[PDB]
Image (cartoon, rainbow, N blue to C red):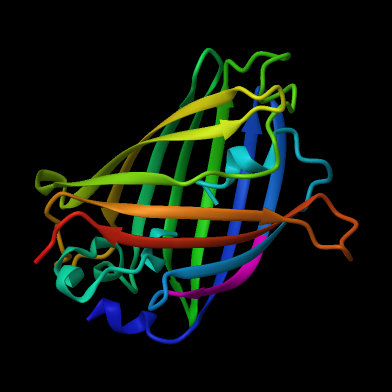
Amino acid sequence: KGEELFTGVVPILVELDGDVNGHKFSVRGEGEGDATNGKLTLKFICTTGKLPVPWPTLVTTLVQCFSRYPDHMKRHDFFKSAMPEGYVQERTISFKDDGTYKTRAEVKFEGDTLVNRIELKGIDFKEXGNILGHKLEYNFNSHXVYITADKQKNGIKANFKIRHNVEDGSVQLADHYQQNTPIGDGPVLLPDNHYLSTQSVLSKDPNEKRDHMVLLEFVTAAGITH
């Protein structure tokens, strides 16, 4: 029944409060998702000024409920099945040979708007690393997000490796460990093992003066043929 809220194009709000090695910042994004095509489009501004980390390090933290699950996989769409009350999504992102992000977020409906509210904390980053050095290129590759059920917690877990292009031509790895738990107390769908397939395009808004990110994301689900 939750899946029903995601026909049509749904409006999206994203709000993040961040602290990275003591650097505090806020990001706000507005946009729209189309779950049926599994596309999604957003513009994010940094409301506290300059962003102390590279925009791409934030992409995965800044709404998998807009994934496109094929008909034969609708039984395994946890994310929509928890709507409208929503879910909490928590993550540890560990950057190789550098610091760690911790994130805690609520994804839920407020009115007709799908809302993602986030707290981010980063520790142990090196000042001259790829992250606080800003050596990361302003782009993004594709990844598989691997999903499994944790039936004991009435939820799901996900694990995946993000590859950030470094300006020197090498790649910064960031292992993602993810846990999602339903906010409401209805039943939800608890998926068999499967994966999301994701791509992001990052660009700029030729009319914006604020530090910002304009984002396009396509995401589909696979991994269980009939």
Going 14% across and 69% down the picture, which residue do you hit?
75
Outermost residue to the bottom = 8
Outermost residue to the front = 169
| Residue 19 picture quarter | top right
Going 37% across and 54% down the picture, which residue do you hit?
197
Give coordinates of residue 104: x percent, y percent. 45, 43
| Dominant secondary structure (helix, strand or loop) of the stretch shown in magenta | strand
Q: In the displayed structure, does residue 222 sit left or right of residue 112?
A: left
User: Was residue 189 drawn as part of the magenta stretch in this picture?
Assistant: no
Give coordinates of residue 89: x percent, y percent. 38, 49
Give coordinates of residue 167: x percent, y percent. 71, 27
Start and end of the magenta stretch? 29-34
Q: In the displayed structure, does residue 109 sit left or right of residue 48?
A: left
Give coordinates of residue 222: x percent, y percent. 25, 58
Q: Nearer the viewer, residue 20 or 206?
A: 206
Tell me: residue 75, above or below residue 15. Answer: below
Q: Nearer the viewer, residue 77 or 164?
A: 164
Tell me: residue 63, above or below residue 3. Answer: above
Going 10% across and 44% down the picture, which residue do you hit?
152
Q: Nearer the viewer, residue 19 or 9?
A: 9
Quadrant, the C terminus: bottom left
Q: Nearer the viewer, residue 122 or 9?
A: 9
Q: In the displayed structure, does residue 49 sit left or right of residue 134?
A: right
